Structures are given as structure tokens and as C-alpha cells.
Amino acid sequence: AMGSGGAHKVRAGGPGLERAEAGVPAEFSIWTREAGAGGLAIAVEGPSKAEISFEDRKDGSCGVAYVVQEPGDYEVSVKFNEEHIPDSPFVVPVASP
């Protein structure tokens, strides 16, 4: 475990939390400048395995690119210190190109 912090203070945004395409990296960002010390957990659950990568932009935010291969309805969960951030999980329809 890392932290007992403000998951309620974390914001998220980006197209990857609205829609995605199969085999195409979906991107969004997580704003944690207000939360402080804690761990970030990103899970994408649906009809296929997800490959999730992250990259701290060292400005209070962290960019996240994920790719799923099967079109369908996925849920993107973003948890800070093992608690959901506001509006998590995110329902994301993934379609074909």
C-alpha cells in the first residue's frame, strides 16, 4: 500500500475516457496536483486484454495511453490510493476503424 490520500481530489480528462478504437491507442490524462502522496491504479476491463502505459508529465498530471483489440463496451477505472476518483469508472465504447 502507498497512501491514504485524496482520491476525491483527482481529476481526469481526454478522449480515451469517452471513446476509443480497436488497435488504436486511446489517450487521457490524470490531474493529481491536489491529491498529494498516493498511488495511481488504471484498469481497463472488457472483452479483451488491455495494455496500459503511463508517463508522468511532471506538471501535476500523468498521460495514459491504452490499447484494446476487440471492439465493445469497456470500463476504464482510475483509482487513487485504491479509491475511485470522481466519475470513475468511465464507460467507453470501443469500435472498429
Image (cartoon, grey):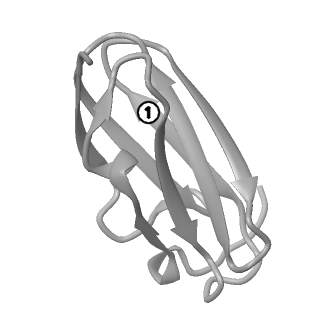
Q: Which residue is mark 1?
A: 44
Residue name at image x 44 percent, y 25 percent: 24
- Where is residue 84 drawn, in percent x and y? 43, 61
Task: Answer above or below: position of 42 versus 52.
Answer: below
Type of the residue with mark 1: Val
- Where is residue 18 drawn, in percent x and y? 26, 49
- Where is residue 91 drawn, in percent x and y? 23, 43
**Residue nearest the observer in this picture, 15 or 43:** 15
Left or right of residue 11, residue 88 in this image = left
Quarter of the picture containing the N terminus is bottom right
Residue name at image x 73 percent, y 79 percent: 59
- Where is residue 63 drawn, in percent x and y? 62, 56
Task: Answer above or below: position of 73 versus 89.
Answer: above
Residue 60 in sight here = yes
Residue name at image x 73 percent, y 52 percent: 55
Q: Residue furthest front?
A: 97
- Graded by Cα atoms within 10 Å as few (under 14), some (14 to 19) or many (20 or more), the crowding at tag 1 reads many
Quick one: SS at disc 1? Answer: strand
